[PDB]
Image (cartoon, coloured by chain):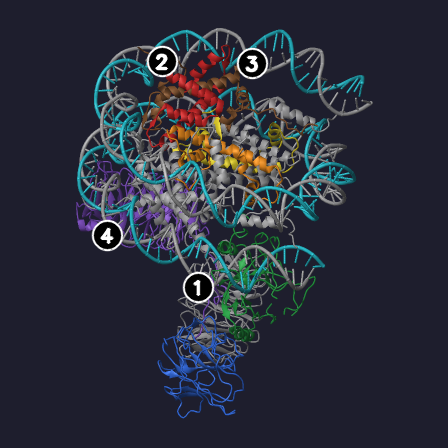
Chain colours: D brown, F red, G yellow, H orange, I purple, J blue, K green, M cyan
Amino acid sequence: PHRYRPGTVALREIRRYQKSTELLIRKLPFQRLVREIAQDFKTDLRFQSSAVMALQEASEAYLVALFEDTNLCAIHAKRVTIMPKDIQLARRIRGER
Amino acid sequence: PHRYRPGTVALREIRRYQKSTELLIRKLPFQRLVREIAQDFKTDLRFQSSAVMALQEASEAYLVALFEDTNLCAIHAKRVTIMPKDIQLARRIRGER
Amino acid sequence: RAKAKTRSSRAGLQFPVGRVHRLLRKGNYAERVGAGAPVYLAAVLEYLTAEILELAGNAARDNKKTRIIPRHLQLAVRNDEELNKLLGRVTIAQGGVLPNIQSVLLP
Amino acid sequence: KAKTRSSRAGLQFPVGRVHRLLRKGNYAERVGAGAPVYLAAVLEYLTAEILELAGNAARDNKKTRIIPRHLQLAVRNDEELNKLLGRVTIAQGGVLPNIQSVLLP
Amino acid sequence: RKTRKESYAIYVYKVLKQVHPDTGISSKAMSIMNSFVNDVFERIAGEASRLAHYNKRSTITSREIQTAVRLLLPGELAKHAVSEGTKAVTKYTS
Amino acid sequence: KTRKESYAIYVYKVLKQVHPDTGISSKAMSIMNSFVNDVFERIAGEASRLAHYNKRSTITSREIQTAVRLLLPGELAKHAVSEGTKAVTKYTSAK
Amino acid sequence: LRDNIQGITKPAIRRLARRGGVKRISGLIYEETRGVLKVFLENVIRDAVTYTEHAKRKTVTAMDVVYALKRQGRTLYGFG
Amino acid sequence: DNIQGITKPAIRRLARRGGVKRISGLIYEETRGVLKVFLENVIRDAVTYTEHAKRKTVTAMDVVYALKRQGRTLYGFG
Amino acid sequence: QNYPEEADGTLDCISMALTCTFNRWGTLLAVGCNDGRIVIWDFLTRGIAKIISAHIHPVCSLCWSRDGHKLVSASTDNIVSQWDVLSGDCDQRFRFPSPILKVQYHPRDQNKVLVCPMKSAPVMLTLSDSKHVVLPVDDDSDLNVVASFDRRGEYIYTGNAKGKILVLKTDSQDLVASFRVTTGTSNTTAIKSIEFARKGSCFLINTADRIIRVYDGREILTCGRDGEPEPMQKLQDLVNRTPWKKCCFSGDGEYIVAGSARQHALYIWEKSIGNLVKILHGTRGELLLDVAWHPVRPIIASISSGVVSIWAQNQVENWSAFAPDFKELDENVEYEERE
Amino acid sequence: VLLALHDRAPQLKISDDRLTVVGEKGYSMVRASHGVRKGAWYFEITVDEMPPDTAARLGWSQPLGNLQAPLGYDKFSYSWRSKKGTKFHQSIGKHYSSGYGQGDVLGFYINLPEPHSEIIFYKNGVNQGVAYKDIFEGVYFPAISLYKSCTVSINFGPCFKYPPKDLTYRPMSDMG
Amino acid sequence: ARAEVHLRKSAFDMFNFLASKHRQARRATSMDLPMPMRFRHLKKTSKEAVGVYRSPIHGRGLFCKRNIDAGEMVIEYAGIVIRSILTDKREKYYDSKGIGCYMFRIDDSEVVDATMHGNAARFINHSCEPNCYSRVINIDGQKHIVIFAMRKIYRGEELTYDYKLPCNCGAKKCRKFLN
Amino acid sequence: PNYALKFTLAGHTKAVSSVKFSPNGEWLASSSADKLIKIWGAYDGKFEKTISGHKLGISDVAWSSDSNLLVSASDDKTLKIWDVSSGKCLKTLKGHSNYVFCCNFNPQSNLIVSGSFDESVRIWDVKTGKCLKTLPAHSDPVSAVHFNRDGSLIVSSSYDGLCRIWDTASGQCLKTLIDDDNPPVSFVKFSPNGKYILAATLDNTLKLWDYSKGKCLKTYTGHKNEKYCIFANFSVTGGKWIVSGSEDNLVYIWNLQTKEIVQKLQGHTDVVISTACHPTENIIASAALENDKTIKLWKS
DNA sequence: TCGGATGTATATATCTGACACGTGCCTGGAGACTAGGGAGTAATCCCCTTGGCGGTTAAAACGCGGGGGACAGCGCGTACGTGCGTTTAAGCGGTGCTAGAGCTGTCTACGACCAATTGAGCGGCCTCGGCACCGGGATTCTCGA
DNA sequence: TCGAGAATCCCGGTGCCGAGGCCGCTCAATTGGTCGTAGACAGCTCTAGCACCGCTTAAACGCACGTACGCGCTGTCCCCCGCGTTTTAACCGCCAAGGGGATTACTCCCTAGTCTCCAGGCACGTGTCAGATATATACATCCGA
């Protein structure tokens, strides 16, 4: 009967995911999302597979960069947990809004 | 014998400077600074006047934008006074460092 | 041999067309500049210039003035949403800022 | 008599295809003669720089075959290449092993 | 005895006297509007050139200018500018 | 059944110069192809805007040199300028 | 269709944050992240369909996605 | 040396324009550092254009072209 | 008011709508569906009036009559039947040679209809029996000939498969006018469909090389047989190069509308001046099928895969009907009322 | 006789000849500060420019009345309408008399022995009607309320143009 | 059913507007900009920002349909700018007709009518606990009656001000006399 | 000018509701508030049948274009739909939260206007029986409704005295007729050009309205118009008479060019509230309230 | 300060299909010779850029005082980790159909170039009227009581 | 809750220099005609994209339990603001001198262009071995003791 003090599994998940390279979003829901929001700009399109792969790569890299800058803001605010106002501050400083 | 409670003169200075348009740095020290750091890239240059004016405009606009984004960061941190770690956080989120 | 009516008022425009076609030839953008592309482009430039000068002149009247100084252009660009999304990284000379005091500073 | 210009300069990237791409792209009216040689030299130096910095991590991860994780590490672990490639997403790239100050107990 | 300079002072002057019959314009605002016109011209021509290079073509028609305007301008301003251009081309046609 | 143009063989040769005992996969080759095309088009665009700024109509090695000193950071710029100047001299000496 | 903005699950944002280096996450980041991802995918897909309909085809090749990302300022190496 | 020309009230007036209520006493040193970095990164490309033109005088169009490459695009000159 | 501007709803009730046409009055709209269903709506209160599931076969052409009672069928087994708005029953039935494209009644008598096949000359019949009058066309080579009546019922304008127009009489075949248009520089091309106005004698030429020309029904009679007239107004497009599918007119010969075939679009020119004045849009990836103008009010009905959209001016509510003595001003209106 | 400096309607077009009132749009009534107390004060009103579409309500009013009171509001102010001669007194509209010509010399008068009244419409000595009767005693400054900006002068001399014949009056060289 | 000759068949009201429902710095008007810049956008906001519905105080009240922030303009109270003795004739006239007095004054020389000509700004009741006030501005001399706000006001609240008879406000320190 | 009684059609067990001719001009059936609708003739009083099957009272009854299909404004919040040639109670219109006083048809004869005592003028159907739209017009119960000549405008007559005119396409107010007094409007109708409306308000003063401008033109004097929904008609068969109900055992019939007291019919024993003319014949219908229960057809 | 238990790194066995390499070949790069035009280089001129001198005052610098914010601590209660059974659609293969991208033959309709004539656009020189500057008094916001 | 005082806002008056317009005078736009080819049109092909089907199962899910953190309050202490007094160099008016920018004339040699001849880089077809996948096992970290 043993349970870890909370935080250690988080730290080893951070090391284990920063080690390797893979894809972190399942490809069938992402493909249905791409077809879903492409439906409203032109009806009856027909995607290749590598285009879906390229969109997945670009979106994942953008999200990871946003989370790093958000965590810098939150550590500046003398806290630990990310709040969504930190995300809004980062997106307003960078110039995207 | 009267002295204001501290803050009111700051607020009316904020309104008075956001009203008008002028140049906020004296032009002789700025001109000597431009000649001083242009000395090390090529000896015996010879500036026009409008180029000095253009450099003054660009530097002043850049500094004002940096101070606005820094004050957004500091108000996010539940404080009032700007610290230099806020400047470093803003310059690291924007991508310049 | 007869009179020659220009290409500026044959379409009912104001920006010139021959000067735009010369600037598309003397630039090496591509080989062969098409037929009516400078007319289309001069119409677009007319529309944008009219759109910004409307707000400029309106603010110039509303500050009890008759000429225009660049503070009015600063206000007219930075008030609207669409032009602020277009002209992102531009420092207008002699521009100035927009009044924005935060919520928690003033008593 | 078939002296290719790559041999006549002692290089690796070809010069005729670079002159073909500078004539086809419509960059200006006339193209000189030393310019594609100069440009092939610059591209050779940049590619040699990136492969030299990739080889270290290629040997350090006990591998004999370069992978995109090696390219990601070799680009991001420098200073000046990290300014030249200012924002470029590399597929199958991965990130830096970074954990902040106050997170550890 | 001076070399001629290309400008846009008279054209800005004409459109201003069409849309506001009284208000004059100084020197500095004229210089700003000159730079603005040159800037938007550079962006649109560059994007159209990159399109016509992508599609294995050699000709900047009006269709590439339309696609460049639709890619560059945000939303409602594009929806007005496309109709203004198409009206101008149709009046020039016949 | 059409011809596509790439840069695989030349990156392969430079790899065999600098590391004589290794090979490379396909994905890294495609990444290096995209990198070479990116740096090429950035340098060519900067040189063209310089040549139009100076009211002339010719792209020479002088403008390519000014484009490189404006574009790259310091040490990499100095080494690349030395490489290019050595290549120009060793080309025009045995013309 | 209505779903698949919610089909992006909720260990997945946790796993993206623990690739990014995040320790403890509140309970609003899920909907905030869904909103941000939807905005970004709109501003890519619109230019992708623009290049497609200008080229006169009826599919969306990878090169159009690379061109839209290149104009936004986020270059992608690995598909051109 | 003569970096002291950017005095204490001038940074204060720039921060009053920026919309700032209260300022500590390290921002002056940080601000002179950031200003010196930015002016170096502009004047380098201005001097590069001037040396390529085979002249001995920095004009206005060279500064405008350097600011265009940085991505800031000053209007009102040239 | 004038030409429409805003979207204003739809009627997405009946599945797979295909074609549409109006009466003289502007209150009757039948729709030949994808399976023989003929559905009429209301316009003032907008309720479905009468479904006529006539054939097991799809319908490709219809037409209303002058009394507001009679219709005409065109299925994929060449069946032409007389219908009624009171009963809705089948009268006539026989088989043509296999293609039937479009029919048209005589305007000042509901005896005669003008029927057009694909690879044959157009044929006029009666409704009393199966009598048919053979109409001669000048070429008789490809036999891809279109024909229509004019407005008042004087002549029959025909259009061949080669680019020459004949003007015949409705019974005696009096060739009284003809003209060949200088189509570009070498090839003279065919005509898709010619339609006619309600006020005057203006009409349009819809070729197969995407150019609309404007003419009158008096100038050709003035030019006589084998004359060379000029277009009163040329209408074309250059940017998207714009293929066409359907052409019709405005209310009292004021404007000209023409739906497209590629981008799901509607364009509104002016017959008076001669310039485009408004572009409409809709769903980006549909396929435009049939466009009908409303004769006494600015309404346009467009079929694109079942959906019938009605651009209807977007009326704006206000005050002054509640209290007709209070005038809602805009700014300060000072005065004295009685001297 | 000069006019007032402060006791006047301010936004009217004050003419520089100091003997001519020029109006505005609306009924803003000037009361010139030299009027009767007792006995007799007669003056004439020479008319220079009287364009049509004017309601030149002329008569008597007190300094109790409003400056923005049209002449013809209450029991103190009197009324003489151009169209159909109508009186409007204590808000009572009764079509009284006829109109009036253009270009004459007008002028009203009250006769009160220190009361027996002559409140009667006076125009070149021609009667247009017996107006009213038996006022109270107070101050009656002359009141001018116009509809246009009509140029109308004023007279004070003893040698009148068309006076009331055999008039008991006092010259304006005593208190004005 | 056809046996009720029943009363309440008189309205005495020209305004039968009342229906069954009775549902109760990003912009320019909340900036620190000069006044006519806000005065332009005043009319583009006020046509759709607020609404008029039935209130428990006196008939119809003013429930706004937008979350108004503190400090900004809302709407203008405009109409016939009457001059000061026609007021008394209209008092006698609307005493004869039986409709109340709608007269706010810009100054003590010229008043502004609302009953004959105006806008939807008439539906503002008096209260002794307001959340708005009034200032007159100078749009090129042609002055106006424009109403600001005081505090942060949400969706579904009545807007009132002091007009300076027992009142139907029920204030904590009510005056109960509107003179 | 010489209208003479032919037949007296009595027999209503309660107060006679309304006399309405056939729209094609051959019937005069008369109903009553006794939940019973009889089918009487117009030229000899030819009887057919009596409608039975209601639950509460009857205010208005209507017709068809062929004078067979029927409907009545029942006072149990319903409008039961009936027939002459079959007699089956066809449908029953729900959707009311108060009593129903009047209903009519467009001339295309497939819509039902419903100005009921729930004060929101709904728009009902005949083919589907479906509430299309709603006109929340008045805070007072509806006295009468009417379409115009083609079927494009609806007038609103109510207690407050506001004769508004309403759109049919999207249903909006166009104009509000106003008055210094507040009389209850009883029963108005349009003109054969749609540009005139005779006002019948409870003030003992009739009015005729210029529609396109908004003024009153020609009135009457010396009449009793006070209590109930007093009806008005037209007459072009004889002179230009104005057939109207009357409370003093008369029938108010006078001409509008003359505006005089020239002919006064008499014979009723209660307040006459419903009159109507045959569209071609010289037949004027007349039926008073509960203490009369008779029908007097004065024929010229 | 010391101990039991899982997770991970280290050491070997087995398969397997990307990677490396060998071949035919066609098309794109090099060699020779010419045209003329963009550029290289001398040659002159004139004004804008540097340099200084003297006077005035607006701004800068330096002390003195205090109250308003930054931060340390402490109590608490709660929202988010860590672990355990299930159920479900994600994923892998196998089979099947076709709309649509891609090549290929012809032609004709549309854009580059040459010479002259015009005429709109730019350079230069008067001239006033809208704003620059400044004394004066009503209005409005502050803060101690 | 009140009064004395201090900045802003508005009005009247002067006056002056830079927008505004006139005048003359040139370079390139325009039309009218030629000549060549880029792209539209049609027809055939064959292969990636979309759909049906079924089996197994990792994991997504929902629900228990604590505990470490977020937050809110309290104190205190320290340091940035507001004002007054003394000082010094920014700003302006002012003149003198000449170095490089700007323009013209005149050869002239550097790249475009056309063809003829060849070799090298690309698609395609086969073996093989670095790594992916298992088994087994020291030991090391963590929370309990």
Residue occupying the point 52% across, 33% down: H36
Q: Secondary structure at mark 1?
A: loop
Q: Secondary structure at mark 2?
A: helix
Q: CA distance from mark 1 to mark 4?
A: 39 Å
The amino acid at mark 2 is: Arg
Toward the viewer: K72 or F48? F48
Of the two numbered discs 3 and 4 in the rendering, the one whose residue sits closer to the viewer: 3
Return the chain for callout 4.
Answer: I
Q: Mark on residue L148?
A: 1
The amino acid at mark 4 is: Glu
Residue occupying the point 27% across, 54% down: I200
Residue L293 at least partly seen: no
Q: Mark on residue D8?
A: 2
Q: How many other residues sit within 10 Å of disc 2, few (<14), some (14-19) or many (≥20)?
A: few
The amino acid at mark 1 is: Asn
Q: Is residue K173 left or right of residue I265?
A: right
- Is the C-beta separation of discs 4 and 2 under 8 Å? no
Q: Which residue is mark 4?
A: I154
The amino acid at mark 3 is: Arg
Q: How many other residues sit within 10 Å of disc 4, few (<14), some (14-19) or many (≥20)?
A: few
Q: Quadrant of the C terminus of chain G?
A: top left
Residue K39 at least partly seen: yes
- Is the C-beta separation of discs 3 and 4 under 8 Å? no
Q: Mark on residue D59?
A: 3
Do marks 1 and 2 share a chain?
A: no
Q: CA distance from mark 1 to mark 2?
A: 99 Å
